[PDB]
Image (cartoon, rainbow over all chains, first blue to last red; front, side, top):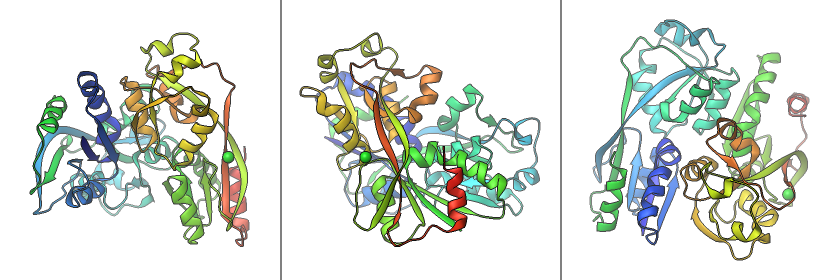
Length: 199
Length: 199
Ligand SMILES: [Cl-]
């Protein structure tokens, strides 16, 4: 058995496709997938409740081995009617918009703070929401703007229900990490599953 | 300060739009929205941590007043390339399909069991997943089929990345409940917001 805990973007928008391909070739090797925020993953790995974790924030622990797995682009986005949805925008313009943020313990929250919000003037947090789908829909209906993985909003961007916002910074790139306990021995079955995770 | 706790279908797909219409008419009156599962909502109401809760399953407590708030259609869905997406299916074919289901004890699993799975001869669960978004991605990539609120799959049905299964069953309707503690009184500030939570 392979027991996995994954962060929100990874567990909801990546690993189900990987598991589908894996189960097709190994239909009699079970997999358990739990999804939470990156802090949830860390604690599950530290408690030896899962075999492997996947996180999307800089989570640190002397008891954890972290290995780079995938790149991931964070995207500032807004309702299509927002003035920010068209043309160049400045950091001061971003700081004047209502921001919708994830909860403490989200890797996305921490990375967005370092890569972007740390460079903004005083800005208002309009709402704090505990998952990325509530944020997507709050932004779609004009409650504010936010910043999430392109993977989370890709389908809305294509359908025109959300709009990407230009940011005067380099592409907001982060690493999606594979983690396991420093004292954990990875099974051959798991290492085989990780081959399906490799792009 | 109105403090809401809502299950995922309601908090992610219904209330964001409602809060928008409300804050547009009451910008000075704030709203705090927490999203989780129905059981999280129940405990938050019991612990007096929120003013009102919204749930999507038959959960019951003797300390709670529950009122039917909205009806909600459950829909069986599959990858567009699935044979089960092409024409009417039999109960036998549904019973043989790989089911992607929410965990036992959740409101969605209980109501899906009652309205759908209890009518199938000896179905098998291909995988258990803890939230609707992971389920959608799993089904989208062919891991199996599932049953969720039409509201939750609407965008993907429109995009054509998920397909509705033509099942030989009645239209499957569940209840979305509004709840509060039985000794709580709905303030006029909250009753006004609830007028915006009125179809
Ligand atoms: Cl019910």
